[PDB]
Length: 64
Length: 376
Length: 195
Image (cartoon, rainbow over all chains, first blue to last red; front, side):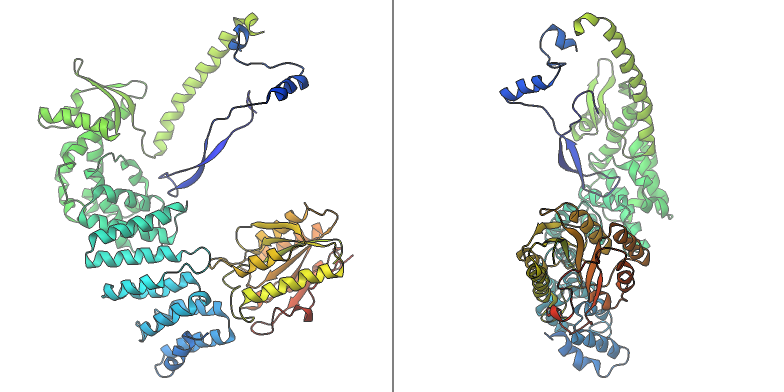
């Protein structure tokens, strides 16, 4: 699912509404990013039959 | 073991009706079904022992020392609680409560129950400051649970009584709204519900920043119940919100009923005017953004110097955002406050968004053809 | 007894805290869990026990280990506001028994009921059908459904035995004094199979 990662990160937030019970326990999304160690990253390339589709680098990636 | 069966034994002999209650209570403990006693005890306090009999004070000691484990903690506060309501001596009632407080084993609803009762006693003496603190403590505990249940209902009744009498309209609104809104059923009488709804409506008019007018209409307490006094009431909620000055003035007699509105007029006059700047912009703007300055003064009907104050006061409280431009004599709004819960609010949004949905898809495909080479 | 994974379900209710079984049930059951656990371990040591609460929102304190210490600790504290909900404990026991630390064992549930059930006649027949198809049985030490209730269990226990390759037993402890900490007299010392 998604064009990107099907990963979402959620942090449990408490907010009041006035439609239902007051003070509800809910999830507000908090930003998800990625990492990777240096050897591990070269490993990610090794399994793929590509490098990556995007990295927001030069002329070519940036448009994609 | 037996604090409670010891007293029960003297008492059961002589007295018809009442003898029976004691006889049943005694047998449960002896066979040692402690739970079964907990089923019996609740009624017993309301039946003999200062409500058919006497020696409730004797019984108050007996329950607390031993019976705090044996008999359910929640039931322990509850048996005394009922007596505290009927009594005309809050000075003795408050001490019994300070002592009752359970925390014996695991989680207890027992703590919250004292907090309403203690608070109610203080208001009756006229310890105003002391009632206010007891409201802050009962609120915090409750709010922590994401739910609303019978003790939660109680909190809302105490908060509202204290607040209406001194006249803190702002402080009254939040509690009163929430009670209406979650649709409380407990054991509430019709008369008590007429009081909640009525006062909340007076309170909004005085208020600052309060645009909770629409949801009130939806809610059962106001909507289901009506009377002759309410016929003024309903109409003032509209007059104030939309900005028709004339309609409110005539309906003013209503202020008289409940003492929530007798504190000020100072903010009251400003507020209808504030509401009209938010309301008017919310209707005509939604992809337009201007409304003329000119309508505000026509929905004010008061002196010119006073208009600048009202207009600026509305940006500040959080009813609206934007700027006012008086070299075009128009009001530009960057933001217009979202309309408090209705079926209508949801409908307005859906159509506009669908129009936008069509723009993204088309534009996306278009741009993709060209710079086909750059993609690779 | 031998090659068994067990979920001991401790009832934690407002009912389970009385003076029914001296001194109070909370102490009395603590003696009772040690005698069943040890009894099964003594027979051949290759069985394990787990701990779940039958009552309210299920919580898994422990998965399979031989350890008696956990059963003894959970039992002494009980919620005042709790009451039995038989359906949640059976559902959860079955689900837990599937995954195991020591994985070879057959599935048997041992449950303490010191409360009258709070679930209707439709519920009790529904559960019995699930227990039977999975061939996972519940042995019940029952004083609770005696308190002011009828013994619903009695019917299920007969049905379940024979067909399932696990056993069910109805063990009767009269309400009020008879002890329920001197378990050797009425066997639920170990869970018996049916095959």
